[PDB]
Length: 97
Length: 186
Length: 107
Ligand SMILES: [Zn+2]
Image (cartoon, rainbow over the protein chains, first blue to last red):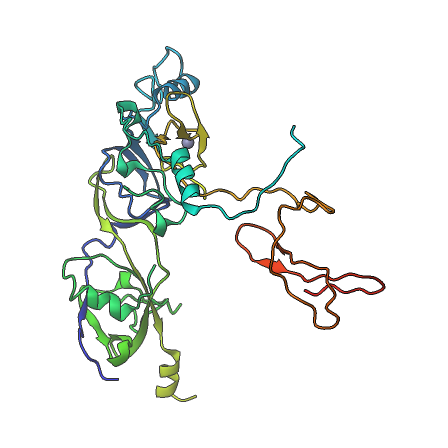
């Protein structure tokens, strides 16, 4: 079996040797791209490398049930303290990974 | 509760069953597209199996590496990202790294051309790397998100994130032990 | 069939609290409003209906055509057939014959 077609070459780039990461989401389909929804905040640590991500979520659209959101807010954050509330409003403003 | 029951077994009419079901469940009220009942079609709940995420409509196939690359050349000719995993150690020796017999790794090589990919009749594939050929096959298929990104640590306090793209396929590369034995008999 | 919430990955439940029924989560406010109809069940379970109408029950089910035996061919056994288990498996046929002092019932 002689080589037929597309006898292509290969090359090595060192430009990003320490700068490259691959990130994978087991719990979400490949077609459900994350690009559209505005990203808000993220955190990293160099050694024992781990990251945290903070993700905006729409509250006005119908599929957000506002009443249950308010109940969750009252259940998770102080009624009127709000000094370090997980959410600025009285509803779920965001969700984290 | 009734006890006196005379059953019937004479042949019935199929279109009558269809009409009854139509009357029972086809009296649509979907015209109630009120604000709080609107559904964004790109926000649906999803089928368990990723490939068949089409539970309600608006109303994988076999593959091989030679096929993948040649469609990636002929039918499409734009850029794409691939994730491939190589043998533990490459044919090269550590270049002036001063060595324990450590395995050479891509992290210890220089830039530039490193070899060629050879496609042979009947679709066999080989990676010509120096004096040796390593066999190549596609990896386990994936259906979930795999985003390629670059981590720019601009400062010890803070840095920057940019997404570069997503990965659609995986490749596995392996030494051809049969070939090595054939070349050097034992 | 089963559903999991895109936002959080847990199973959905079905409920009504407004003009229209809803598919909802139990941990996050994600919900979908069902305006249409879906057509697949869990195949429920109720046991063997044997003596629904045991014994010489009503005569409405009488019929004309019948088979015959290979050995003797006496005048009394009209046909009947039955089923195996559920909505998606076959149905069976038995030819049982019975005058006295024997054991016949052909499959
Ligand atoms: Zn939830």
